[PDB]
Amino acid sequence: SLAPEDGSHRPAAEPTPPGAQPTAPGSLKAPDTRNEKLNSLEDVRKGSENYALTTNQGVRIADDQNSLRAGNRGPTLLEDFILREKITHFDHERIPERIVHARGSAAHGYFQPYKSLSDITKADFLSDPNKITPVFVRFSTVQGGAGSADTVRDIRGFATKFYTEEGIFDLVGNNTPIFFIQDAHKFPDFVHAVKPEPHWAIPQGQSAHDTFWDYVSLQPETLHNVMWAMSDRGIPRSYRTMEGFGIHTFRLINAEGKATFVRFHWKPLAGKASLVWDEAQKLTGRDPDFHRRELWEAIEAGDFPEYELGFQLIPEEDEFKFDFDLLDPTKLIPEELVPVQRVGKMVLNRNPDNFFAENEQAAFHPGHIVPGLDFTNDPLLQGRLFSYTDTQISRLGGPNFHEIPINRPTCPYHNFQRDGMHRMGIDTNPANYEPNSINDNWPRETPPGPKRGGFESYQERVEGNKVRERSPSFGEYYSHPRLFWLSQTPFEQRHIVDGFSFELSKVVRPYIRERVVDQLAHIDLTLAQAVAKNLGIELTDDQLNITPPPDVNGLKKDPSLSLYAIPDGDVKGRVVAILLNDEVRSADLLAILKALKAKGVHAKLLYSRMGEVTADDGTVLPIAATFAGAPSLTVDAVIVPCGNIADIADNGDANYYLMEAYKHLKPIALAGDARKFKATIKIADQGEEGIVEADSADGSFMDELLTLMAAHRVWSRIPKIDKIPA
Amino acid sequence: SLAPEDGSHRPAAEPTPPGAQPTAPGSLKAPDTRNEKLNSLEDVRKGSENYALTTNQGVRIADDQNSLRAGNRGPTLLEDFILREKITHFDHERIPERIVHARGSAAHGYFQPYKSLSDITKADFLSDPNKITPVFVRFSTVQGGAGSADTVRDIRGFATKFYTEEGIFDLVGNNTPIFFIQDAHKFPDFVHAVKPEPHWAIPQGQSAHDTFWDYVSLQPETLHNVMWAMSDRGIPRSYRTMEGFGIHTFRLINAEGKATFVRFHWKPLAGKASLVWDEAQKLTGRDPDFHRRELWEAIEAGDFPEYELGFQLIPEEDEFKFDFDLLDPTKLIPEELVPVQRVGKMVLNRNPDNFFAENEQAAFHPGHIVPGLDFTNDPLLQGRLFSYTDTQISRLGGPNFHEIPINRPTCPYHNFQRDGMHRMGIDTNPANYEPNSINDNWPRETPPGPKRGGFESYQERVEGNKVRERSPSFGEYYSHPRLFWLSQTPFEQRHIVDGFSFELSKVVRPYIRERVVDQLAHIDLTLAQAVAKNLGIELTDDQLNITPPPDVNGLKKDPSLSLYAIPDGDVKGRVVAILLNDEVRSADLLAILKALKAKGVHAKLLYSRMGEVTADDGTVLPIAATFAGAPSLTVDAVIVPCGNIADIADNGDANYYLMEAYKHLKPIALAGDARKFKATIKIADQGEEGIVEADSADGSFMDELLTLMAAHRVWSRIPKIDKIPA
Ligand code: HDD
Ligand code: HDD
């Protein structure tokens, strides 16, 4: 027995805040969290406790420490079948990673609609407010490999597998409402341009290189999503604090056959929140797994990520009433023109057991729709339908990928397909064809109907010649980037300018920079001049005379496009760093932890070493991490309680901890003699907005601090940070 | 035509310093750098200029911007074979990454022995000083995926494919002289333990988690390589400044049939040099491709990585004359007892053309030996022989992986093997078996002999029972960790302490830390006490009376195990940051750049924006990067010339540039009014060692700075950096 007698090796099977316990597989951490999909996976789950170590053939292994050899110092013998099996499996562990979105993090949950949508869709999972549909959701980046970092500047993926009673429905979206390109034929072109360059495979997880901006400068259709990626949208605080969109216009079909155009939205319950770039870039080095960890730990804490599903709904006769083409995925539908209507809510409440088996092997594909839903002629969606079935043949080893447990439907599935690599199902049907008499033609077709019917495509009208040709209605590239730009706050605009500037500064060929600046001058001259200034470029008089693009159906801004314009913050699930000293004033800490617990805010107690310290009243305080081990990048605010401040007053890591949080605009709270730290951040004796300070942490100290946290960051501090050396 | 009329899209086909030009595939950058392997690859190289865009079947494409559809706003048609071919190929681009060493960077070069070694080996590539052997070298980390970061704390791989006239020889080594484990049966257990943990797949590129130190604490055989991993050996400055080792004892076999035991060594011509931890960890964020980048650019500069091959040689009759077992791969051979004898030199002088085709698909395997070389009963080596063949069947799609162009021998190869997936060779032999009369038994066996003879194994004697048993001679675990500890300088010992301390602070279960500390007390109680203090752990009296382990055949220490104890630094290929202002003193800059070119030291001119600035004499200075875009992490030293210093005196990024470089112990030179920056780094008016300063950048000023660069870092500055907030 190698476990410790005190049993401290096993985490408790109950919700615990991040860092209190070792993380564990979901069925062990929360065995009583169940749904119909989790239960169906029990047949393939494998335990371990009280079992013998065997080969894959069931043979008990006596000595798992040594190869078989001719003498204890002799050659290894080919007849060691236990070695060779163990090494063979190891030698073939890896499978191809996803072509795009290879880096991702996933969890189980459930979905439930608010009310029956049977008036607009016959889709069964939206027909009754009491119908609960299990889900599996994978969040992702786009460009980086499976081993790349979480907090890069990138688009994020948001893929939801609905295990419906009438088929698997995959909603395969991103965290922005549009994509970079218009036609699927260009997808390898765009992806090759953004991916690491083919001679040397640099850089990983970054669009800040020549070939990406080269493609953008020559393809202005890309400009809208590029705007989004250069904003703080491209660097989310977590997957819980981002939006989701299906991007394409789809169709809803009701029992009477009426089609309604629809676009899908996920609204985060935790609000919209993003990092700032210096923080996001450094965090890819201090913790490349930050988003993966934060997701797992929130679920282990009970901080279940929640999202409200919503629809923008457009009648068929309104197809042409907007300036933009509904079928153009580089165009958004402003919520000011078509509101998002609440449909239901999704809760992610259990982690997987084995990342490889459940996350890496999961297969999402937007062609996986159910009766009540249908496609449109969006030329990007159209080509997606081919790719997501095709790519699985190599990634997941063949055509039986639906038999891998995480991908199996929970509803019945029967047909006349047979064979293929690693076929699990053993068909007893006398027939493998239809029409057949020898099994009385079963399984049988089902006619279309209002529920439990067969799938039939909406009989939309088609008219035109066979052409490789872009619809002229698509050939407008600058109005929607402008609408986005004007909808941002001034500090969000600053960050957009700084994103473009930082990225173009790493383009080596200067003529590429100049061509991207010229495209910006077609969007907004304020934006283009600000970027040009940082690049040492001067706009020509002709460029200064570029007429701006028209408004979007009269709109000159839409505050739903901004992260922060309308407050939607939420402190539940946020984390505060508490910086300890060797004789902490316990009255401060008790007030701090009481206020944080009331709002569901977590705390990390940090010191210069691990182990424990003792407060003034003798209370023993366990240390979560060092100052260097858990930098301010990983928390939302910093609190410094009173006590023996001289212990850390001249500690470089303690001082830098506050300087980093200050530069990154986070709230900071100083109690008693901890107010001496204002000098390291150059805060005058009069104080300033964003620095909570008082004689002690009792009173309004923590309400000021929690109000600041509900506002996410202290945007008013931005003029002051450029003098801070951090 | 989309290129710029001035041709600045294309880099010059001549050696150019890093940053000067865009990087390029090796055949375009250096068309005249040739060897036999590079030349043999011309049959599969594909150009591009002046060729039509086609399908894979050779059909010319007219519109590569659109899918085929029924009307320009209609559905995509299944008959668009151009779309489906292009998407199909994209959908299947990825192949399994390597199970280990998935992250790596490679280059072409050549090798040449100094003299004939026919007295000790009949290996043909070592027979003649005028015999040139082309090579392909891949450097790697171990734990992370192909998309993980370069400057992690890990072991590094160093793999060399020799394309000899008598077969491919692969020398597949690492950058430390031992491995973690003794018997290959344990390799899946160790690797699984160091890799991301199976439930959530965290952490990437790090051994700082519970399962790794759990294994270590339970398997003391691992302590020796762990010590190397926790030293600055784990974080190399670049692949050019690290050693290589084969680790295993092999045999040399001469024409008389005499066996000599040998261990292989690579000695870097650039010397040994490593980062510091805070620097290395931060650099995985600011540039996760730092090592890949530095290697490519050094070769484009003509700054070819060079390595001397050396042998430790031991007569067969001396097999048992050491305190350790020569066949134990957790033991090193001290150079003080067996010197490394120089054999030849290897030069890396051309980058690949396509990273995937040459680097990702390259297959290295230590079973690939040639006549004149042989194996030993090293139980780790013995199991490696199985794995490197087996793993390619899935990783490279089958048994013809030797036909992938990078892997092809340059010498003849003929046998009776046939078929298999993607077979390229078309065999005309009437017979696919031997013995055969119908082709007069060709191709035929060759008897062993002095040159050009068939491979025969050394007929070593084997005596023993079939057993799964570790040799008792392997049962010592602490003498070699001690030897290594005592061989380090005081500041390398400090960095080892901080490496163990940092990593154990990330282990969530405290009993694992305590168990690792107890292991450390069997090596050195000063190391154990210093790590325990940072963990809040108090060693018991029992632990304090653990007897130290004996030394190694009388050796207490061996300075060759230190990175820095013996000076070996070379400044050629290093890089200096030069921080500009808007009116630089041209006399300063002229003298700086003149002295750096004399030593082959590169420079990047940094400013607060892109573009150009003008010197005091009107000289236009082009800016290479911003202060933030090329942080001090990426340079070896910082020079601040005199000028309009008020322009950057209050720039937070400019002051931080110096503070970061200061903390990471790098040389700093300050001319004229730049000396006012001393206050930011808290240097007294009278100065200190490591800070170069004068009225101007002439005189001895550049000599002083270059002397500091030859010493790599200012170790004496360590006591001062703790009080620095950076
Ligand atoms: C025609 C090619 C093509 C095009 C135009 C798109 N995609 Fe895609 N996408 C793929 C081809 C693809 C793929 C190559 O088939 C992937 C990679 C691995 C896989 O299974 O599917 C994929 C993966 C993938 C994933 C990750 C699913 C997971 O977690 O496993 C998401 C979230 C998206 N895509 C979302 C989008 C969105 C929102 C798009 C624009 C509206 C989009 N893709 C356009
Ligand atoms: C029995 C299993 C096993 C054991 C005990 C080892 N390795 Fe290994 N090694 C492999 C199984 C393996 C592998 C799984 O076969 C790899 C991964 C993919 C491949 O082609 O070979 C590999 C890759 C690999 C590479 C990367 C090659 C490349 O650049 O493509 C290097 C440098 C090494 N190894 C070096 C070592 C050293 C120095 C070891 C100890 C002395 C060692 N390996 C033990």
Image (tube, coloured by chain):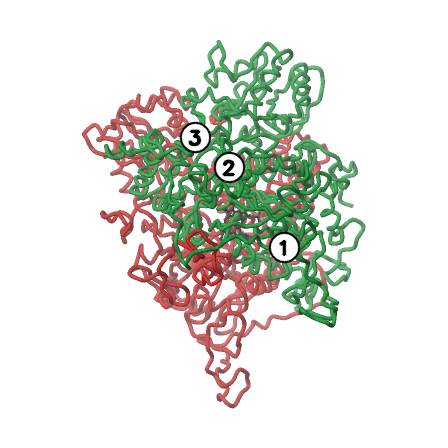
Chain colours: A green, B red
Residue designated by label 3? A555
Q: Are marks 3 and 2 in contact (CB under 8 Å)?
A: no
Q: Residue at x 64, y 17 (%)?
A: A584
**Residue at 60% in and 52% down:** A368
Report the Cα–Cα distance between label 3 and label 2: 52 Å
- Residue B181 x, y percent position in the rendering: 62, 53
Closest to the camera, between mark 3 and mark 2, is: 3
Pointer 2 indicates a residue of which chain? B
Report how far apart the C-alphas of labels 2 and 1 lie in the structure: 59 Å
Q: Which residue is mark 1?
A: A455
Q: Amino acid at mark 1?
A: Phe
The label on residue B277 is: 2
Q: Is residue B227 visible?
A: no
Query: Is residue B72 left or right of B213 when viewed as pictured?
Result: left
In the picture shown, does residue A503 fall above or below A397? above
Along the viewing direction, whichever of B111 and B563 lies nearer the viewer = B111
Q: Position of residue B676 (x, y in %)?
A: 34, 21
Looking at the rendering, which quadrant does residue A262 occupy? top right
Q: Secondary structure at mark 3?
A: loop
Badge 2 and badge 1 both on one subunit: no
Chain bearing tag 1 is A
Determine the chain carrying the residue at label 3.
A
Q: Given the image, on which type of amino acid does mark 3 rest?
A: Leu
- On the same chain: label 3 and label 2? no
Residue type at tag 2: Trp
Label 1: how many residues lie within 10 Å, few (<14), some (14-19) or many (20+)?
some
Element carrying mark 1: loop
